[PDB]
Length: 275
Length: 91
Length: 243
Image (cartoon, rainbow over all chains, first blue to last red; front, side, top):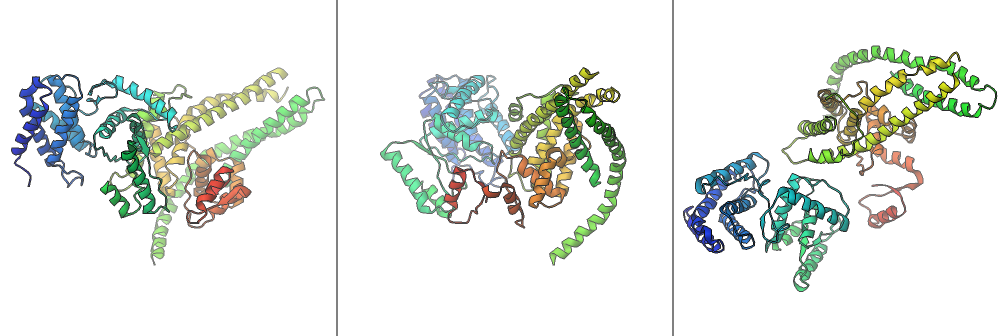
């Protein structure tokens, strides 16, 4: 089974210990971070259960996700203040535990929880608005992964979307508060070694367009399976095989957008699993 | 009921049809004899037509609230008939 | 609201009672919020779409109506200069025609809120029942009542967007007499920024649209073999297609 909640606290201390070799000025902060991460985990697991939503399923893999998500930000960021690191930690905490959260009652519940945790383990008055909308971290504007300015980001997206609008398919849209937060979310996903993000967007939200965009910013070939009523598994197999052979033997760097419509049978989805 | 909304739109389309007929002849028969007068007796007929609309708009404000008074009784009839059709549909 | 605002950024409008742009956007939100709340059942599967297309209908409809209001206002101003040149017995009644000139300001007051209803009919109503449409209309009218926009109290969607020449053309093909079936046909034709989905058990509609486009009418079905190619031929040379 799972370990302790006190072994988990201890195990991730050693995880933070290793990554705080890169911020030695906060070597004394590894334990309350490890205790906070585990607290956040224990609480998310408790507050958001499979009784509300099926995908509400937490495990120490989240912890490992968070701890590594923290390192990668440090290893490629500006030399860090304590106010930085907790916000750096808080960003990952949001992306790991709360992106999956539906609706708003539960989403606000986590905002309060995150606040409750910092106050209990890392007591500072230097924190700001910890809501995801207010902490925006990016490597689009800086060479180092750093917290960016809301005004600086919106304008950067605006100049790049027109370009993407001109260079690629011509579709005009309104760039808005939700969309900036989401652009960074896809960006982090498409940056990590294994990058798999599934977007749950109703329809016309723009989820398919943003994906094409952020992929273009990251310099990814956007492959979209050309399926139809009279498409066989063999067709999809071919679409997949090519995209695989190009990725290794041509070093292509493709982004495969699969819509729910594209999965025509059981096997199609099984192929996606094996991948 | 049918002619109320019919002649509302028809007379207004004929008011736009006669304004065009007046402007066509005023520009053609300015150097000719006083023909415009032959359309002005049709514009004298329009004094019924312009005010026919006023006659119909006045009786509309009397007809509409009576139409809405008659929807209620038929609603009482109407609501039972669907429940009956539903029942016969279900067989 | 962020998205609505940038879509109505183009400003045909003129001062009203109370902001004017701020009011319009707040109505549409409060209508979309009321539409899904009353009509749709099931827990939060569906979200904003009609809203975008409802705004896009309004922009296309206000532009079409304000340019036609200013066109009829120009047709009575050109007749004002021509009667003043002449001045005799009947012509001074014609001059009096400030009742119409006075009437224009009241007509322009309501055109913004009239376009609100027309756009809502085209977008939200297409698939609603006789009673379902009327009832939403009331909720829209009382929303138009809360906000300081003026609407026509004696308003009729058919007469407002259908022209008597077209209304005749439709029936000539063989459209049914009913008001419901008129509104439906108007919704299909009037707006074509989007492909229309016609649902009718009796394929009496498949002929109606065929009579209207005639030779140009090429009929297909998603089930036939040659569908894949026959559509590519239909698209290349401007063929009007029903699937």
